[PDB]
Image (tube, coloured by chain):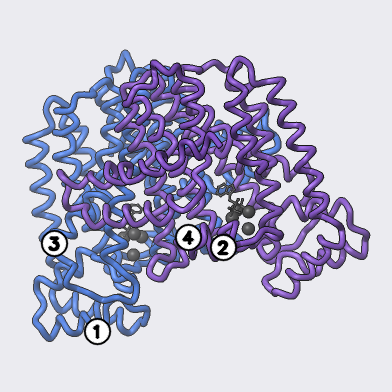
Chain colours: A blue, B purple
Amino acid sequence: DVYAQEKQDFVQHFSQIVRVLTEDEMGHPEIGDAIARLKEVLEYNAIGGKYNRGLTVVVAFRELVEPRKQDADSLQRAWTVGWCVELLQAFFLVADDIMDSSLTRRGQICWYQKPGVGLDAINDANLLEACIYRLLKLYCREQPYYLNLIELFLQSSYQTEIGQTLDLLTAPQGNVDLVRFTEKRYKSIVKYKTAFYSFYLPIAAAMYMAGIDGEKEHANAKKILLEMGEFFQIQDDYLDLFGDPSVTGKIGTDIQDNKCSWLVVQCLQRATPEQYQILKENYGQKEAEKVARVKALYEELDLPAVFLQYEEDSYSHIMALIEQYAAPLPPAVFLGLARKIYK
Amino acid sequence: DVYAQEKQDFVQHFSQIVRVLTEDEMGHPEIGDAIARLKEVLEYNAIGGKYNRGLTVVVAFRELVEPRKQDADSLQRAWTVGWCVELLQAFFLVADDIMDSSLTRRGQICWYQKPGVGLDAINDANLLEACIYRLLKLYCREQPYYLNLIELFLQSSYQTEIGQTLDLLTAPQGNVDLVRFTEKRYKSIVKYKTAFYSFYLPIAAAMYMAGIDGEKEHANAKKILLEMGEFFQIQDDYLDLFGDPSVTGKIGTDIQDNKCSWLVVQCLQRATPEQYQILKENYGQKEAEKVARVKALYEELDLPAVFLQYEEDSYSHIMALIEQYAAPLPPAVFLGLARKIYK
Ligand SMILES: O=P(O)(O)C(O)(Cc1cnc2ccccn12)P(=O)(O)O
Ligand SMILES: O=P(O)(O)C(O)(Cc1cnc2ccccn12)P(=O)(O)O
Ligand SMILES: [Mg+2]
Ligand SMILES: [Mg+2]
Ligand SMILES: [Mg+2]
Ligand SMILES: [Mg+2]
Ligand SMILES: [Mg+2]
Ligand SMILES: [Mg+2]
Ligand SMILES: [Mg+2]
Ligand SMILES: [Mg+2]
């Protein structure tokens, strides 16, 4: 992949990110303990993933910016902005893990589950968020795209938070109403909670850094990226139940948490009234036997096979959107991302 | 007060703030339920306070901007930016109430304690934060001070979050070490957690709106405002134990929560080794009888009288700093604020 060609170098740069964020300390040694906590938080929560969102900024930048304009400082700004995307993810995930009552993330216990962390993780997440704007000021403040990037991160955060609200509102604890789990509702939740920040944000950041600021170009980019994001969230929902946690790094909670998962939507489209009652009886509950019954029902209704077919159809659709909407950007910008997510 | 002269009108404007924030809905009716939740969150959490921070932007604006430049639109931008300060407070308090295990706020149950809210309040707080940047874009994007304000809110949030980290790190649950509760540590915690966002932020916002952007003018302003903020937090700590909750609107938790309160710092400065052991035995614990013992010890050591004296000395000090540092701004800018907090 073009992603493996940039990864080791991207990751390498995290030590610099941490160093520049945790040297607000000469000048202000009274905040030392707080900066030590920030370092711990950064190291626990922004490292251990695949780095695909941050890497996408870097790879897109190199593909959109003329090689004679890819000087040392410009490349550094590019991987800084990719790390800002990673930090945005880190902030959101820390908070999400608490609100979803999750156990593990990236092959370790969730930050909030750590003895001695707990709900202090809320402020830790806010700090991760603040680091984004700190790095943008330190590295990009004199660039013509500075305000574009600040506003792109802010707006992406707002959209994401709106999607989180829909997610949580459609999934009330102890309150099983399957009636709300429609395809239309599903598409809206995932557009807001995932598609903007996971797909549109990183490419858009690289577009703005390359001086591509036009509303038409950004709107065309979105046509591809929001669709890619929807697929990505459907995949996430499928892996929540059917994925191997040694590979995914995380234990699923969607059934217990009463979530408007792609799986439950597809279940409802297919289920006889008898299967509907089974689903109603067992969904949204902590008991392991009830979760098992839901999984059994999904397997009975061939949902893994339905997912496999959906992934093929989706891949073909996204490739079609690249043919329609890529120009004037290099198709490789989107195809690389397609390759990474449809693996 | 100059604050009462602007309050009814300031509060009046909240209906407009809510209307403009909850009409992201024509165009995007798929987010309707989320926008309904945002309205609920806004109404519960940004209304019911004294509005002093938001009001300070408005009053300072009128005192710093030439009356011929105080047109309809400019006044509207001023009360919008004051509401942004209120929203910053609202975001921070929702999160703080969870992390401090608080019960009530502004004479009602804390948002997170509401049946059916719970830890979903984390995302609600993030949404309140997003509304700040939304209102600044909608109302101030074409103004020469736009980036100044965005960066002032972002930086104030970072500082505040650093202060929150110090607060929480100095107050580990179930872990009583009084050794860390020093005056030096106290001053650092409150500078970061309170002084920036409660005092410096609102005046600074009005300064930038009035085209007063000079580093020397902002640095002089800070000399007064950070000191005022320290006093304000000492007052907050005193009222945590000795205030009337029908007046304060909130039930105190500092002793239970093992906080580096001004009260405990002053206790440690004065306490015999026998009183030190009593404090060690009873601090940072949930039992009502142990909290009562700590309060008894404080009363034994005349801490209310010590606070009364401190408030006089502090008032005199801040007035001295106004004489030194107010120019070239009208002294009324600071004196009005002094009047409100030393009441
Ligand atoms: O927990 P994961 O990794 O399975 C999850 O995929 C995480 C996720 C998706 N979108 C957002 C937005 C903000 C915070 C977290 N987000 P989900 O949406 O299923 O919680
Ligand atoms: O709960 P209160 O109102 O007594 C409290 O005064 C609230 C407070 C002060 N400073 C901050 C910063 C962020 C969030 C809340 N903050 P405290 O600092 O004592 O928690
Ligand atoms: Mg989750
Ligand atoms: Mg979630
Ligand atoms: Mg998931
Ligand atoms: Mg879940
Ligand atoms: Mg508190
Ligand atoms: Mg607190
Ligand atoms: Mg307090
Ligand atoms: Mg407390």
> Element type at marker 1?
helix
> At label 2, which amino acid type do we have?
Ser
Q: Which one is nearer the viewer's eye here, B63 or A124? A: B63
Badge 4 and badge 2 in a common chain = no
The quarter holding residue A84 reads: top left
Q: Chain of mark 2?
A: B
Taking the spot 50% from the left edge, 40% from the top edge, the residue there is B4
Name the N-terminal-most of marks 1 and 3: 3
Left or right, B148 with reference to A303: right
User: Does the numbered disc 2 mark a residue whose Cβ is under 8 Å from ligand 7?
Assistant: yes
- Residue A281 got which mark? 1
- Residue B102 got which mark? 2
Image coordinates for residue B216, horizontal then vertical, percent: 61, 16
Q: Which one is nearer the viewer's eye here, B309 or A178? A: B309
- Residue identified by numbered label 4: A110
Give the label, 4 or 1, closer to the camera.
1
Image coordinates for residue A224, horizontal then vertical, percent: 15, 40
Q: CA distance from mark 4 to mark 1?
A: 29 Å
The answer to whether residue A32 shows anywhere in this view is no
Q: Quadrant of the N terminus of chain B?
A: top right
> Element type at marker 2?
loop
Badge 4 and badge 1 in a common chain = yes
Taking the spot 68% from the left edge, 65% from the top edge, the residue there is B256
> At label 3, which amino acid type do we have?
Glu
> At label 1, which amino acid type do we have?
Glu
Left or right, B227 with reference to A307: right
Mark 4 is surrounded, within 10 Å at the Cα level, by few (under 14), some (14 to 19) or many (20 or more) other residues, namely many
- Residue A183 got which mark? 3
Q: Chain of mark 3?
A: A
Q: CA distance from mark 4 to mark 3?
A: 30 Å
Image coordinates for residue B302, horizontal then vertical, percent: 85, 56
Give the label, 2 or 3, closer to the camera.
2
